Length: 480
Ligand SMILES: *[Se]c1ccccc1C(=O)Nc1ccccc1
Image: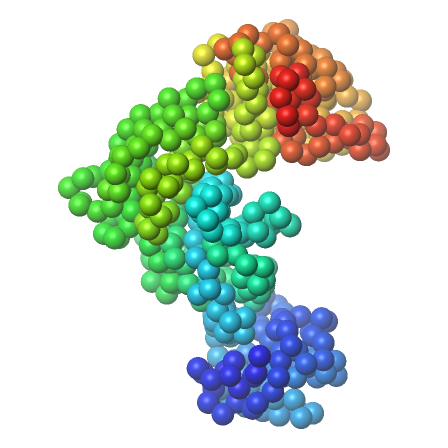
């Protein structure tokens, strides 16, 4: 890494200087580093130029605004300081060149939208790896190669993608928030494809701001959920975008690329998805639960078909796709009730989990749950009301009561119900889960909500060893 080579596209005849790491933070700027002095909200990195110089940085790139002309080369204590206009917008490009353009050295797929970014990125990474990629994710669960995901500026994004390239990643599925795009954190990334899941005078400015940003980015092939009203607005302006539907929103008059589920059977162990597309037709056995996860799966499928993965190979590997751990994770055993373990610990997440479980449920829907102690009590009656409405049998139990009287939490939950007397209450959580699993019929579904993969139960100050997944697996005679 050399300052002169790094700046060649923008500053001819910048000085020759070996560089170590690139940093926005004067505090971690070490000998041989490139310090980048940016203006943010209130913060001005140009204040820290003397400190960075004293810590032995090789060179500094600084915001030009009010200070210097674009491309102006100064020399301070023998350290080159080069000024650039609009440094915040150009940070992604500068870091991309610093880190040897990692988005040109693997297949990068971005996913944006309110919901389904995590699931859709995990399905892209899993499916591509099943077809022979070495796949990675960058998202809210963290970054890394599949199975080794460890829990953020334009530089950090480029640096982390470069670290995955260095680890041998050939495919990366990246969550991209609306806020991420606006703050120029992915401005210079070359996406092979980008995915739109959903959105949940004003409408004119919003569209105009997003169209402007999009026109500036390198998003590759567009894959868009045509069941979303805003998604259809976007498709109307993007004739080469792939339209994806499970609710009959493909308009075949367009002669564009498309994929649509013609039939979905939600059964006790997942979903049978029959689909047609401009690549051909097929039947997928998904091990994921609910309508939203059909959509997320169809977006991943359309994306990988669009990038040229063969339909026959995608169909052959679909049954190996796994749920995101602790997210609508289904446990079935021969002639036992279906059990779903989900992390839902809010009124909205619990209602969505119950509505998703209900589709797979021929019999009674059971809901085992509780609420955290020594935290906001507001959600408790609202979660009671949700369990009473959207489940057939509500089993109210403990979930991390901490130092609060466990029964007091249960009382606050029951107070939200029309008929508290209809609720079942059982303390010990292990006991309550057992009661549901052992009483439920073969065609029932038991939702165990609130913990997902969070394998402890906090009682007083003790983090007790406890897993919903292990409890359920042992009762069903299967392996968590
Ligand atoms: Se641009 C980009 C880059 C990464 C991830 C997502 C996007 C994006 O905005 N994609 C998109 C939005 C709406 C319609 C099609 C595609």
